[PDB]
Image (cartoon, rainbow, N blue to C red; front, side, top):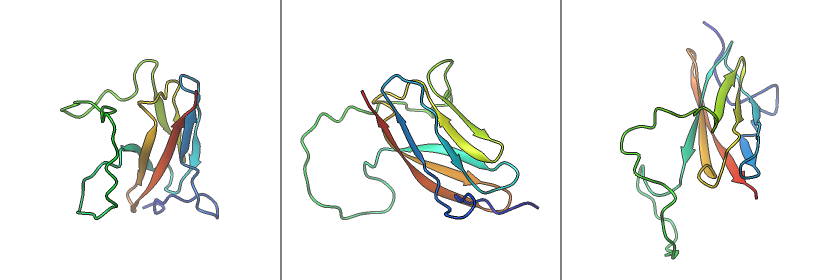
Length: 130
């Protein structure tokens, strides 16, 4: 009995989902969203490797090491550490402010907004500068 959730703000409906930091610096990200009063914007991460349905991308065997991820095995439940990353949802929007977004955080992310009326999704681009 509220408003339909959506990745929109007041008109252009364009959430600047872009978290950037200078490698080990205090970064703050603010993005307005729909939903009322407070929706559920979960900040998800994306490594664009190869999953979900099938796909026929371009054959570009890129030589590399392939060791950016790790063996988390179970599900990482401890997200916000004591002083590593702080992600909280404001009263009517999502905020991504982390003071340690290193190369391990760089890559791509997919934030999802949900509520009792509906749900939406979007991609967040990250970039750690030195």
